[PDB]
View 1 (tube, helix red, strand yellow):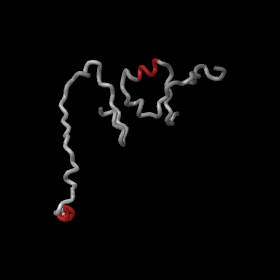
View 2: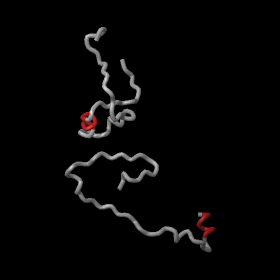
View 3: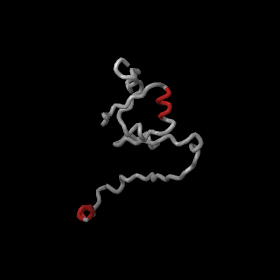
Length: 50
Length: 50
């Protein structure tokens, strides 16, 4: 916060991480809602971020 | 039954519904031994050639 007014950076401890994308993509609706209900969820696969 | 087999590939199936579980459907499965054709026969040479 000393450098940016607001940033996409967080410090939550992950839980029940997903192996890689295209598995979260096709899993199911209202089935992944339970994953986010229990807490943060992390996706491991590298991305092309700008 | 489909999900149980772990023979060679990862089978994934989405959860169906809370109300579509009791739907009925017909699926036949042959139950006849196939080991009685592989006996020693006096005509096996023809089988091999053809």
